[PDB]
């Protein structure tokens, strides 16, 4: 029960309203004041029997009006539901905020799908128990103490004995609770993780579906998916062993009442015993259901308490034509296994520098550090007399547009994907022009409208060449100081590619552009070419210097001009 | 008529009705007790007092009978076991109709929805099926039970209640049919939006690159909370059940007191409150049945769908037939036949190719080729017998297609390659298959092959790495027809050559149809095909294009003057 304190604390912060809870707790006492006053008041029946007809015709009308108070008990149940629907939406509001602001490093260690269900399915665990959490416990403890005080006036020795029997035998309820906590956590972890599994097979059905998908993927889905939700059978098994344990704790009190009293009103003392036994069941299940919610929500607090990414610190310099620099910059996704090892290069402001290296040699990872995603292990980047964390992140993005390797698409239309950034600042005239430079506009027009044709799940309704150019157009819309293309014309045809490079050349004359290219034939006229092999920059400067670098580094034209000489002859 | 598709699916496809009988057995036993208590406990003031004369004989009247009082708890477990089986049962079912489901579905209703619409939709019925029967059966037993006792002591006013309560229970249907929609429509809303929150999270590495952290938080806040608090309207309707029941008995008070002997008058109103308690138990079950039917309404619609598997035609016993086309027209949107009337012959064993502009039907023609979609007017022949009379299930076993996108999933490098029917492969086969894709040389670098998780869509690996693994997967299956839809797009020209050289040795006497961005890659391709705006315009080796067509030259000749400048200044 030391695992109650760390989460009840978060339950408290998670509270947009409380005043409604008071109304539920007000009527709860009113109604329990009735049921404990019923056995003392309902002992006179002859009086009503005689005045059953004459008093019922003139004074008996008021008896029907009392169903309003009996109906007002239903609005108190609504208070448990309204504060339940607010506390469920409350945790939803909270966790989501610590996920969008969450650093990129988290999605390397802990999977995306895993964080989704432990946000939607985990929250719904507490809702179906918070409506009976307080409701069952409060009315339970009121009547337990209530019936006990009446018994304390009636008897002092035998009444005291129960208080040393039931709470001393309630220590056999903790192994039910402590094994209920880990039994609902493991289930709301294993299947929380397993929603995610279909979320990796189902969208990729378009590729997955061949003789591999046909049945083999049903098994991962079906065996794991079923055999792991049927772990709740073990949860329902432990829950059904509450009842006989409570029936066995009162038996220890029977020896402390009959065996102690009888040897030393006896019939009257055993009547009230069953009146405490009913709410005893109400209190006991609340304890187990509180551990059931703490178990489930144990994942929420750990995910909530995390180092978020900073937005505004020191100074927010928005307009500054700054040259990019590097000094002994080393980085790795794991301390023992590093990717970049002390790299230094100067990118001149205004002029288009480039980066070319073999696949798996550190280009994209250097650019991740560039668009400020990760922190270097030993080095830093020289910009506006600041390093990485102290300098403003919001301002850093506000004037820089980076189109990474992958073509990024989400649900909605082409308009939504481009108008992603600086929201409601862009007019119709701006998009048309931004998409024209990307060349996409020509074929955005072909299909029914720009704001009409939807992309779908990761943009499957559109071709590679179209989805790539839209991503360019998105960066073109913001008009940034530093543009970026990490193999942006990879699947894009050489004829459909030239038109793109020609438009960005006109725009970014007095503005910096750092690009990555698969074929050196594209980045022939690049101001400062950088060769990225196995994690360090080896070859610098234009093609006249690259051929003069080393023996191994000669492929700059050597491999591309080979397959070219064939067409001519 | 929406009740029937629930219980018929709950029966003939759901595993239950076993332990259910035991729960329904003890339910009658215990309700036979509570209706016999007011008739037997008439002399309980002496009944519970009779154990005084017997002495210590209490160890058989109460002590042993707590086993039967404890056996009621195992009957509650029977609801739970049949509940946990019926929930897992629907889960087993729906998943099967999703993997076997055709590609056309994920164009119209998307995945995100259909994913969460299983796992969250199934859990709606579990927390109600434990009190569904439990509350209704014990309810209806005691209602009829107390009513029959009222008949022997009263045969006039007892009949009046039966014409009051069920005639006033018609004000419970507007609660029920407005309870069906309020769970259904919300079980769309959540699923659809919670599935939409799952699209933003994996692509975060581009969310924190654009000013959109708070913009997408704003989609989440006003979106997920905005519609989850629609359950407030669901809990609102549910809390208006209680006063309606309290008001239906008031209509009976006029039909009992106002219509109705004076001694029995007090006795008739006592039993009235004994029916009123289980009345509440029956009424909430009706609303909670509509709550489950509403939720499960979209289960059945998703289950009842046309699957993707045939039986016509067996395998071919390792024989490569020639690929053909005759007036083949296709278009997702029936308004625009995107891939118009097309005819081309691909020679068996020969490495033919396809190159056209972006948006002109290459990949869409290959989707039809991999035989996913059905052509609107034409058909595909494979050795003068069409594609159809060989089933789909076997077609893919002999054909390996590596489409445009680089496909990656949660598993390691081994699980991605081994994917084409796992455990039917040995260690010697993978090593060789990965060597041909020239990824084996890069896998070795990192600690082990089998001990290297790729992650959510393989973010732990680079473009050049993830592309070659996909090629190795097809290389592992040793197929008759290989395919590369710009498989060397992000791949470096130096790291690319090694790949093309290995597949040239293997696919000598086996067909290979490829798509290329740069014509410089597919220079020596048997029969090049130009795919512009949906129809094949150019045919054969690029030399034909550079002489025949007067609008496809500058197109087939671009890659020549592009890098013709690399040997101008250097040499
Ligand atoms: N989470 C990670 N993200 C990126 N790279 C990682 C990660 N973990 C390890 N790596 C290592 O980084 C390499 C990829 O780095 P990077 O993306 O910069 O390559 P690249 O030079 O840009 O080549 P390509 O053009 O193929 O993407 C992997 O091959 C792997 O060794
Ligand atoms: N669901 C869909 N799937 C694929 N294509 C679609 C879909 N709906 C519409 N289309 C249209 O079909 C066109 C042809 O698709 P396809 O991928 O084959 O083009 P492509 O010529 O191969 O270009 P690229 O090589 O750049 O991908 C797309 O450009 C798109 O406009
Ligand atoms: Mg990269
Ligand atoms: Mg394509």
Image (cartoon, coloured by chain):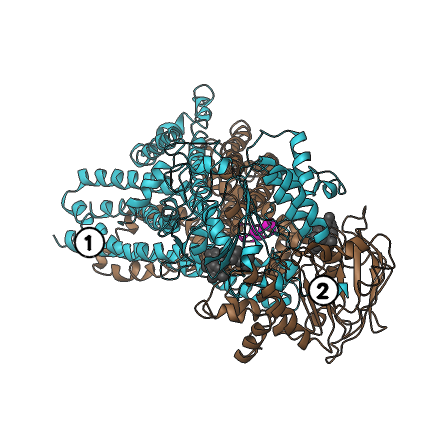
Chain colours: A cyan, B brown
Q: Give the range drawn in magenta.
A: B112-122
Output the chain of dot 2.
A
B546 relative position to B4: left or right: right
In this rendering, is residue B18 above or below B569?
A: below
Q: Nearer the viewer, mark 2 or mark 1?
A: 2
Q: Residue at x 66, y 34 (%)?
A: A431
Percent x, y of residue B454: 50, 61
Which quadrant does the C terminus of chain A fall into?
Answer: bottom right
- For the point 70% across and 45% down, the residue is A499
Chain-order first, disc 2 or disc 1: 1
Give the percent coordinates (x, y) of residue B137.
Answer: 51, 51
Residue B280 drawn at (x, y percent): 49, 40
Q: Which residue is drawn at 45% across and 67% down?
A: B446
User: Mark 2 near mark 1, Cβ–Cβ under 8 Å?
Assistant: no
Would you say A273 lies left or right of B191 here? left
Residue B550 on the magenta span? no
Position of A50 relative to B490 (above/below): above
* Residue B116 included in the magenta stretch of the image: yes
Q: Main secondary structure of the magenta part?
A: helix
Disc 2 beta carbon < 8 A from ligand 1? no
Q: Which residue is drawn at 76% across and 52% down?
A: B360
Label 2, on which residue?
A565
Secondary structure of the residue carrying numbered label 1: helix
Choose between B406 and B138: the one closer to the eye: B406
Going by the picture, which residue comes out furthest to the top?
Answer: A58
Task: Report whether the residue tagged 1 is closer than 8 Å to ligand 1.
Answer: no
- Quadrant for ligand 4? bottom right
CA distance separating discs 2 and 1: 108 Å
Identify the disc placed on residue A258.
Answer: 1
Q: In this view, does A312 lie to the left or right of A172?
A: right
From what the image shows, is residue A300 above or below residue B408?
Answer: above
């Amino acid at each position: 029960k030391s695992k109650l304190k760390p989460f009840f604390a978060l339950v408290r912060r998670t509270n947009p309203s409380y005043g409604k809870l008071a109304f539920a707790l007000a009527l709860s006492v009113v109604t329990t004041l009735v049921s404990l006053l019923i056995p003392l008041l309902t002992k006179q029946l002859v009086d009503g029997f005689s005045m059953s007809n004459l008093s019922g015709t003139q004074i008996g009308l008021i008896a029907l009006v009392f169903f309003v108070q009996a109906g007002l008990s239903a609005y108190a149940t609504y208070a448990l539901n309204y504060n339940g629907q607010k506390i469920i939406s409350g945790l939803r509001e909270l966790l989501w905020k610590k996920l969008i602001k969450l650093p990129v490093s988290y999605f390397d260690t802990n999977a995306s799908g895993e964080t989704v269900s432990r946000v939607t399915n985990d929250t719904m665990v507490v809702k179906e128990l918070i409506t009976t959490h307080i409701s069952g416990f409060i009315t339970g403890i009121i009547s337990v103490i209530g019936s006990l005080t009446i018994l304390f006036i009636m008897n002092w020795k035998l009444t005291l004995l129960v208080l040393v029997v039931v709470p001393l035998a309630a220590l056999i309820l903790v192994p039910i609770g402590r094994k209920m906590f880990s039994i609902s956590r493991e289930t709301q972890d294993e299947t929380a993780r397993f929603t995610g599994l279909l979320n990796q097979i189902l969208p990729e059905i378009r590729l997955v579906k061949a003789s591999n998908a046909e049945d083999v993927e049903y098994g991962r889905g079906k065996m794991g998916i079923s055999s792991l939700f049927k772990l709740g059978v073990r949860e329902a098994k432990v829950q059904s062993l509450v009842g006989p344990l409570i029936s066995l704790v009162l038996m220890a009190a029977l020896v402390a009442v009959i065996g102690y009293g009888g040897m030393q009103a006896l019939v009257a003392f055993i009547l009230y015993l069953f009146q405490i036994i009913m709410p005893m069941g109400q209190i006991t299940t609340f304890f187990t259901q509180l551990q059931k919610s703490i178990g489930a929500t144990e994942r929420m607090i750990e995910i909530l308490a995390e180092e978020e990414e900073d937005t505004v610190t020191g100074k927010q310099i928005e307009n500054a034509h700054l040259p990019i620099q590097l000094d002994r910059v080393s980085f790795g996704y794991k301390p023992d296994q590093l990717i970049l090892k002390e790299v230094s290069a100067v990118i001149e402001a205004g002029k288009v520098t480039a980066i070319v290296g073999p696949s798996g040699g550190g280009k994209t990872t250097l650019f991740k550090l560039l668009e400020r995603f990760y922190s270097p292990t030993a080095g830093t980047i020289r910009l506006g007399d600041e390093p990485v964390d102290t300098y403003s992140l919001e301002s850093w993005r506000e004037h820089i547009g980076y189109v990474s390797q992958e073509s990024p698409l989400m649900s909605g239309t082409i308009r939504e994907n481009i108008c992603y950034g600086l929201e409601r600042d862009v007019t119709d005239a701006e998009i048309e022009k931004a998409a024209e430079m990307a060349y996409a506009l020509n074929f955005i027009k072909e299909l029914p409208n720009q704001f009409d044709t939807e992309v779908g799940e990761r943009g499957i309704m559109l071709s590679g060449g179209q989805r790539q150019r839209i991503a360019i157009a998105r960066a073109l819309l913001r008009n940034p100081s530093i543009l970026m293309l990490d193999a942006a014309t990879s699947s894009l045809d050489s004829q459909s590619e030239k038109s793109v490079q020609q438009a960005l050349e006109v725009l970014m004359e007095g503005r910096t552009t750092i690009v990555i290219a698969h074929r050196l034939s594209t980045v022939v006229d690049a101001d400062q070419l950088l060769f990225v092999e196995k994690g360090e920059i080896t070859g610098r400067g234009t093609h006249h210097e690259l051929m003069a670098s080393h023996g191994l580094y000669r492929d700059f034209a050597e491999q591309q001009l080979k397959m070219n000489a064939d067409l001519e002859n």
